[PDB]
Image (tube, rainbow over the protein chains, first blue to last red):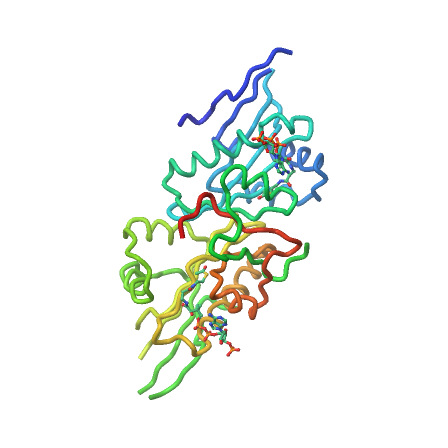
Length: 148
Length: 150
Ligand SMILES: CC(=O)SCCNC(=O)CCNC(=O)[C@H](O)C(C)(C)COP(=O)(O)OP(=O)(O)OC[C@H]1O[C@@H](n2cnc3c(N)ncnc32)[C@H](O)[C@@H]1OP(=O)(O)O
Ligand SMILES: CC(=O)SCCNC(=O)CCNC(=O)[C@H](O)C(C)(C)COP(=O)(O)OP(=O)(O)OC[C@H]1O[C@@H](n2cnc3c(N)ncnc32)[C@H](O)[C@@H]1OP(=O)(O)O
């Protein structure tokens, strides 16, 4: 599956998917600010990105970063998906689903068979719709003294 | 907390249980250890790849040198780690060793400044992790798998 794909063209702009890991940490910070996520040191955001097995992006080209998902992984059995995000201006258009499909497909192409995530209650059904299953066989996602 | 650690010294003949986060596991011993606890044979090439790309590989060894325990974690090196493949040789279970292994793993991840330490727990070991300070579904967060076949 190619690194870059055009997911959509509309008249007014195209929406570009990429798995090359092309994220500017200021862009990602500004996007994270829109959904009100608290800021974290740019250098730590940068470190988290280059130590992610998969960094996937949505861009708006007329490049504007409008979405992103990333995954840690051991490159053999497991990947865990983090920081899934779509610009609120671009939500409700199917782009978040389209991002996650290409993410899942890229991981399966790389022979990662155990694809996991920790879903906020608000977005559980979004992932179920994509085929994720909570607590299969009673397995529990657990956190060491979380600060949530 | 150092790289390598005598957790315990005992007699029956003198045995030491040694902790290490160096990550120098012999993949063939790890393969037999995986087999001993009843996990299916995985290809050597994929197990080794999983070791090399694990941010943390922690072992327990018996020196009288035998691998008797292992735990590993993936990480993004900054914010998140997920712990996988915690196992203790059945002949060494029920001795506090799994607890001691996990405590050293948690401390190592904390020393590396990882805030979010996570894992997915089989329902029959959920209480084992609760006893170490893990919490299931905080704020209703759910761990999810894509079309799992367990
Ligand atoms: C990273 C994690 O592991 S936790 C998840 C992180 N998410 C966040 O908290 C960030 C904030 N939210 C967002 O960025 C966005 O709302 C997203 C990523 C959650 C969703 O992306 P969007 O672009 O809004 O969703 P998109 O339009 O693609 O939605 C597609 C489908 O999901 C459904 N859907 C969308 N949002 C939700 C939701 N919150 N709950 C349930 N279903 C949903 C839609 O009905 C649609 O269904 P369809 O296939 O039947 O048409
Ligand atoms: C791998 C993952 O990511 S999830 C883990 C799934 N692993 C497995 O199912 C494989 C098989 N299990 C094992 O290898 C071992 O049983 C382990 C790792 C689960 C535990 O190791 P052990 O060495 O048996 O445990 P240890 O003796 O250290 O026990 C620690 C404490 O937890 C308790 N405990 C041990 N096992 C369990 C259990 N299954 N459920 C609840 N409590 C337990 C013990 O009673 C002990 O309590 P105490 O300190 O109050 O006396």
